[PDB]
Image (cartoon, coloured by chain):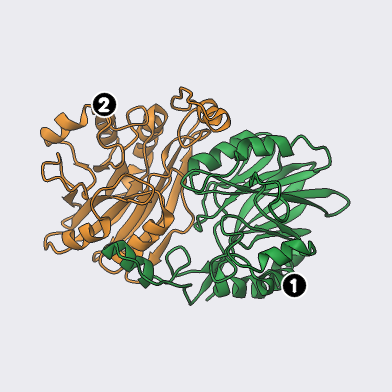
Chain colours: A orange, B green
């Protein structure tokens, strides 16, 4: 019924706000989905990351681009206990973990699936056709899709391609929340990017000095996660009978 | 002191909302900057498009990526009468038009500059250093930068790179407005993407079927400008002493 989707947790600052704030608004929701693809120092997710998240009220953990950058993801996916969803369109049959999980919110079924875009990114399986295939299952219920992609064109198409057959399509990866939050004809909440959960004053999550120096000198520079004030971006959703009846952004910036 | 920036005008739907709606809000501003890179059927700017926009109340026409897709842009730039500003970082010394224009607003000078990003785009001159060079002049007054780019990393960086020495840095080209509207320390308004002015129900401005079929079949499809309701996005700003003291998004969706 009432679910909150939280964007890309980026390193400690991201983990910090997430673990301090989420619990302050967790009661107002029935389920909470969190994208943790940058949890571990900006790349991948580590064991502490996942623990901290779940302890905070996170019901589902989605990944994406950097799903495999930290060595902890394999044992976690292997010992299948944490509610983790990684990109579904990874075609290799032997890919660890699963591309979708269905949960029991309140006697109702909620399926959270994770998808990867391809434009301006590495090539994986066709996300559009992958979805047509997952949608031919029966046990799904209210379906939530986290489309991790760069290109706005590719994100908007997934929204129209899925409108009417999914409850929501929220994009992630670019780190800046978009103001196009809407409900597409058919009852499908849509927003090109939820925005991320990390350092408020930064360059896509990195310390400002590094990237600025790369852009200027065109030579490599070492860079780490930005320090200081952190922000948390997400989307508050309201579903009924497998569709979205209300969708609005949620944003908190720590003092 | 009061200026409005309107995002990428896209085709007839875009020109329709621009021309019908601008004149009713125009009174609230001293100057209005409009990006017309997609005026001509989604690609470039033709003479009518430019005439309509100016008649509507626009004082400056910025372009970008597709600044040259319509032949009309060469004679228009050659006769140097319409207030047009094309990307500054085109290194060829013979490239038509200019990379900036300073206008007399209310006893003060307002300089509008158009810049092109390079990530996930065609290589042109370095925008960061191209700005360092422009910024060495002393007759610019209040400077406004329209950074036409794809990558959120390159946009956030240009914002940190110009904070404190430009009144505003508003990005364009991605068509979806961002919700990060902020005034960076040093008095610099910033927004990763103004959003565009064109068809509300589409894929980046194109009709939904064409691009969708491309995405699904991976085979080329003929696609054109979408029809139906048009949306108009912009940023209303308040400049004072070369600095931004107020910035808020402007959005309108026709019924």
Q: Do the residues indicated by labels 2 and 1 lie within the same chain of the protein?
A: no
Q: Is residue B239 above or below residue B221?
A: above
Residue shown at 35% from the left, 32% from the top: A19
Q: Is residue A243 visible?
A: no
Using the image, name the chain to which the residue with label 1 belongs. Answer: B
Left or right: A132, with B248 as reference point: left
CB atoms at circles 2 and 1 under 8 Å apart?
no
The answer to which of B225 and B16 lies nearer the viewer is B225
Q: Nearer the viewer, residue A217 or A170?
A: A217
Q: Quadrant of the N terminus of chain A?
A: bottom left
At label 2, counting other C-alpha atoms closer than 10 Å, the crowd grade (few under 14, some 14-19, many 20 or more) is: few
In this rendering, is residue B84 above or below A6?
below
Task: Give how far apart the Cα atoms at labels 2 and 1 are.
Answer: 60 Å
B166 in relation to B228, above or below: above
Task: Report the chain holding disc 2.
Answer: A
Q: Is residue B215 left or right of residue B23?
A: left
Residue at screen point 51% across, 33% down: A202
Residue B66: quarter of image? bottom right
Q: Secondary structure at mark 2?
A: helix
State whether residue A47 is above or below residue B17: above
Label 1 sits on residue:
B55
Q: Name the residue tied to disc 2.
A: A48
Numbered disc total: 2
Relative to A135, B118 lies left or right: right
**For residue B158, which numbered disc appears in the image?**
none
* Place of residue B109 in the rendered image (x, y in percent of width and height, measured from the top left): 83, 48
Q: Residue furthest right?
A: B107
| B61 and A63: which is toward the camera | B61
- Quadrant of residue A96 in the image? top left
Q: Residue at x 58, y 64 (%)?
A: B69
* Residue B248, percent from left and from top: 62, 52
């Amino acid at each position: 019924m009432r679910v909150l989707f939280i964007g890309d947790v980026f390193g400690q600052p991201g983990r910090r706000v997430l673990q301090n704030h989420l619990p302050t608004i967790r009661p107002q929701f029935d389920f909470v989905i969190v994208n943790m693809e940058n949890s571990a120092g900006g790349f991948g997710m580590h064991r502490d990351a996942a623990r901290g998240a779940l302890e905070a009220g996170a019901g589902c953990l989605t990944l994406g681009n950097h799903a495999w950058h930290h060595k902890d993801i394999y044992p976690m996916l292997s010992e299948d206990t944490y509610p983790i969803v990684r990109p579904l369109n990874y075609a290799d049959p032997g890919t660890p973990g699963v591309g979708w999980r269905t949960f029991d919110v309140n006697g109702e079924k909620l399926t959270v699936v994770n998808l990867l875009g391809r434009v301006f990114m590495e090539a994986v399986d066709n996300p559009f056709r992958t979805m047509d295939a997952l949608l031919e299952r029966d046990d799904l219920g209210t379906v939530f899709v986290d489309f991790h992609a760069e290109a706005t064109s590719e994100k908007e198409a997934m929204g129209w391609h899925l409108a009417g057959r999914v409850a929501a399509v929220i994009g992630t990866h670019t780190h800046v929340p978009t103001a196009d939050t809407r409900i597409l004809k058919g009852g499908t909440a849509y927003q090109t990017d939820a925005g991320f959960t990390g350092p408020h004053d930064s360059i896509i999550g990195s310390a400002i000095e590094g990237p600025l120096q790369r852009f200027l000198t065109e030579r490599p520079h070492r860079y780490g996660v930005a320090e200081g004030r952190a922000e948390l971006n997400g989307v508050a959703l309201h579903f009924e009978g497998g569709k979205a009846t209300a969708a609005e952004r949620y944003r908190f910036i720590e003092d």
